[PDB]
Length: 465
Ligand SMILES: [Co+2]
Ligand SMILES: [Co+2]
View 1 (cartoon, rainbow, N blue to C red):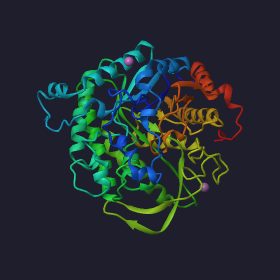
View 2 (view 1 turned 120 degrees about the vertical axis):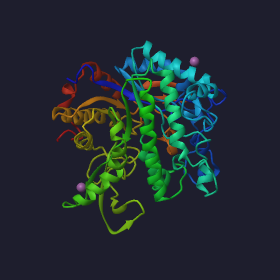
View 3 (view 1 turned 90 degrees about the vertical axis):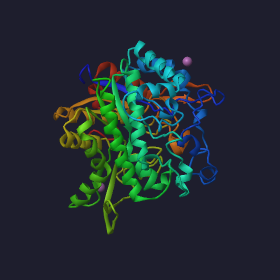
View 4 (view 1 turned 30 degrees about the vertical axis):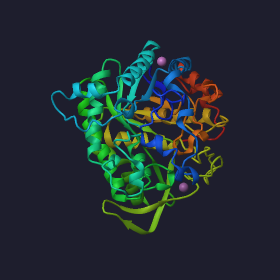
């Protein structure tokens, strides 16, 4: 059995879930880079973004009580939710310095209606018996922090997002403000979510449709380092107001080489994708949030590319990992999701071992899930990834929970509503949430704290390791 303290739950963000009534001006958060990005004509006409709009979404801002009750009804004991910086501080905090009197000046400029709303939502979680896990940043940034169109077009701006040295400083102010206001109800803190994704998709792998979509390898590394500085500052600032655990939620990639005897490229890819950032924050983490979807298979680049800050001597092989046919199969034979992501739960076991060996911190799986609107695989995904967790734990790895991504279908960034990751189907016309069959399997595992009753049926051969 998993320990009674092991957390079963789900993860959500603010932007992908909160909005749902386009005509409520207090709910409509017009002031993020992402909000404007998804309606940009260049992006729309070129299919860089989907055409779907987040204000037509799942309506967590208004329907939180029903979503919290769904979570308890399906056996969850914890939800991780996002707070949008843009909602708390719609206007710049750049004129309010660190020091004596900072918190009171920030309270005078903060959007207290948003602060009170987040409070109500977390009070509801608490009333329902759910542990409150707050993550302070989840990709979106306030428009006074990031003007993605000025950046995209190379036009002068101070609003450079994570490239601006001002950003980590303002973020530290925001983190301290929130910890000061909510230290009495938050059980667990994360500074930010998948910072390597923000940096890599923003400034390096610019075919994913993320802001500012400006290829600059130096800005890739700079935004990554500025995010690590932001985390470190945030940890110190939150800890002024609480002794509760503070960590970061990171997207880890497992790499397999195409050919044997390529350990150099393995270590290079692991460092760039995982260890570069994590080594910068390692002195200021009480736990590591492991987000895991699939692996990448890599091979040696005939001609390495040298950048100012790093060498690239490998490339990503098509047909495995994140690079499979959407709704098809990997070259391995494994099914792939409707995002083209191979089912590879052994990657999570390998990473739990590697991460624990490197850092020796408690781990929580903070995201794992699949784009699967017909529920073809999601039960086996849950079971086989928990099999991975159990195997790691059996070998002495300290894992404290599993939060699925996600409890409901939501707005998947540049793909919009086209990728459906929910345990429950979201009817976006009625704003109602209908548990898929896999959500009953999740409830069974959470309630019994076991997968032993599932293990002997393995139709996709996912638990043979
Ligand atoms: Co309300
Ligand atoms: Co292979």
